């Protein structure tokens, strides 16, 4: 009854991760993937595996987690929802200056418990309308078990840097002095620095960092902030960070050759797809097993808006994500030539 | 020194059209096309053919036309520039409630002459100062008299509501509709669309068919087609996103399916329609060619914009024959065409 992430069988769990696949076409009558299939990971199952559920079913870690919050809240249960693209039932108009951060912070004062769900779905989530979010993209999800003090400290950072667009909150009787309450009130883009990083732990003791940029930041979020904060290089060499132009097949006909693919087949999830059909808001380091899941994608071109990423160390998840790389060269080209075309997208 | 479109040899011409190719690559070290190559058409040459020039050269119809305006203007020469994405030297934030329209109206009051250049480049043009080469684009440039340019300006003030920047009035009287286009656009438009008939100085009839920000229907099938009393040729248009499709190696990939192919016009390139601004269309009969501000996507913002429509059997046939359909692996031409039509769904 304390607020907690829920796993695939509705059991309380300290942390979970999911990678949802995009909608993928088999033929005119059927999809290979609807876009709600996913792989699931937590440290109890100990492996990244294909889920038997669809994410929009009323089953699986996402539903069980959010239903445990919204379904029958206590007198001191509350929540903060935010999204730069709010769902249709939101209680405010859009503010285009706020951060491109999306998520849910839920809490219960009496039990001193909280959770944080990070996702990248536009128009999600709603506390009373099961909205149908888009199936078209690969996406990642991270859900963490928190104590109330950690949720408050996180909300204080977000009020300063990420500056999320908060909608339909429930305060559960919070003191107006609480940073959780302050996050529901108007924000001031005032901080003099351009970034911030904080250390936290889950209730289970798993260390993580929240690494944020604000509207002043104009450099490379990944190589100039995240990497240096982790004291490790981001593994970027096969990232798509811009557009590859159409590539010649033959006789002057140029086609999309994606070159870089994300491949989950080693995890029992029988799908591989272009990185351009992926939100690509995760990254790993080349050493020390850091996994980052967050608000900011891999494109060199970015807006001057707040946002951040969660970083934590996980050898098992790091290995699984490392092994999702798939490089397919265009016709007549080598692997080295394909890698050079990918790296060219890193040029501004 | 009367204002006029200039052709590929820097001679005055009543009308010209250009189709610029996107940047196209062979590998990381070589490109098949820089994205400044183009085919050119006017009624004097009477053929749609690849230009010897690049559009960023200090020659060719685009350079010669704009240089005849910006290069050494007389005291009565002026211009209205507009773009929903203003260039950097405007030093102003964009107003997203104004129209998609991009272009240049230039004029000289002493000679009662004007020209209209329609283009689709963001952040362009600037009277003193590199536009993206990444997309296929169309251009149209028309010779107008000052009265016609003012009638067009009056329509724009109501419907397209273009975002004007760095104007030069050339001493325009403030009661001119051209001058009003440089002032804040506050007039309320009646209805959600408008269509007007015009002619070039050379007598070529054209229509300007415009929607305003209250329009929420299909610009092409519900406004343009009915205005022209013809059907738009849309059956192979990409009007939405096609998901990745399964290949035999077990991986899902981008298959473009619909390509734009200029090889029969001497330009040895074909490319995905998704790498094309696709702001042109033709009808199935009566030889209508439309070049404008509005692309083919079903999803549209509620903002102003329009298209220029005129009849030209020669350009119509050239554009019609640029279709190229390539099915995904294992699929037939019929299945490919059904996948394209699927992008037309609401």
Image (cartoon, coloured by chain):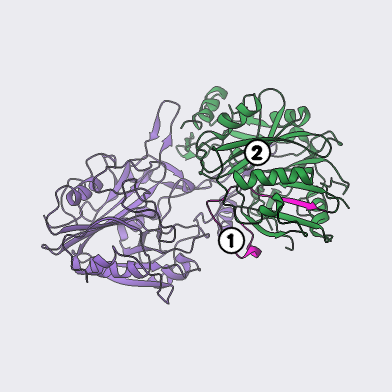
Chain colours: A purple, B green
Q: Is residue B309 visible?
A: yes
Is residue B282 magenta-colored? no
Q: Residue at x 31, y 64 (%)?
A: A313
Tag 2, which chain?
A: B
| A262 lies above or below A75 | above
Question: Dot 1, crowdedness within 10 Å: few (<14), some or many (≥20)?
Answer: few
Name the one closer to the observer, B308 or A26.
Answer: B308
Q: Residue at x 77, y 60 (%)?
A: B171
Residue A347 circle label: 1
Question: Dot 2, crowdedness within 10 Å: few (<14), some or many (≥20)?
Answer: many
Image position, residue A179 (x, y; %): 25, 69
Which secondary structure, mark 1?
loop
Q: Is residue A117 visible?
A: no
State which quadrant residue B250 falls in: top left
Image position, residue A234 (x, y; %): 44, 64
Which residues are the magenta region? B86-109
Q: Is residue A246 left or right of residue A122?
A: right
Q: Is residue A225 left or right of residue B173?
A: left
């Amino acid at each position: 009854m304390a607020i907690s992430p829920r796993d695939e069988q509705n059991r309380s769990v300290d942390l979970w991760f999911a990678y949802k696949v995009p909608k993928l076409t088999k033929d005119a009558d059927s999809d290979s993937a609807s876009g709600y299939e996913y792989v699931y990971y937590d440290r109890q199952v100990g492996a990244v595996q294909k889920s038997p559920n669809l994410m929009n079913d009323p089953k699986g870690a996402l539903f069980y987690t959010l239903d445990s919050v919204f379904g029958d809240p206590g007198d001191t249960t509350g929540w903060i929802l935010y999204n730069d693209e709010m769902p249709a039932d939101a209680n405010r108009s859009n503010n285009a200056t706020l951060g491109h951060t999306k998520g849910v912070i839920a809490f219960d004062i009496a039990s001193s418990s909280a959770l944080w769900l990070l996702h990248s779905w536009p128009k999600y989530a709603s506390p009373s309308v099961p909205g149908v979010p888009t199936p078209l993209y690969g996406q990642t999800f991270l859900c963490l078990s928190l104590d109330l003090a950690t949720a408050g400290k996180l909300a204080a950072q977000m009020a300063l840097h990420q500056q999320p667009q908060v909608y339909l909150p429930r305060t559960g009787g919070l003191d107006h002095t609480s940073p959780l309450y302050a996050l529901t009130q108007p924000l001031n883009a005032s901080a003099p620095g351009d970034s911030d990083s904080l250390d936290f732990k889950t209730r289970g003791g798993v260390p993580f960092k929240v690494i944020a940029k604000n509207r002043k930041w104009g450099k490379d979020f990944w190589n100039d902030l995240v990497g240096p904060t982790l004291k490790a290089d981001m593994y970027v060499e096969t990232w798509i960070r811009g557009k590859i132009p159409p590539v010649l097949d033959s006789d002057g006909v140029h086609k999309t050759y994606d070159i870089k693919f994300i491949d989950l087949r080693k995890l029992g999830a029988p799908w591989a797809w272009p990185e351009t059909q992926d939100h690509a808001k995760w990254g790993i380091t080349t050493t020390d097993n850091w996994v980052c899941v967050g608000d900011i994608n891999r494109m060199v071109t970015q807006e001057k808006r707040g946002g951040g990423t969660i970083a934590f160390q996980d050898p098992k998840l790091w290995k699984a994500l490392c092994e999702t790389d798939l490089i397919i060269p265009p016709p007549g080209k080598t692997d080295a030539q394909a890698r050079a075309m990918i790296r060219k997208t890193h040029e501004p």
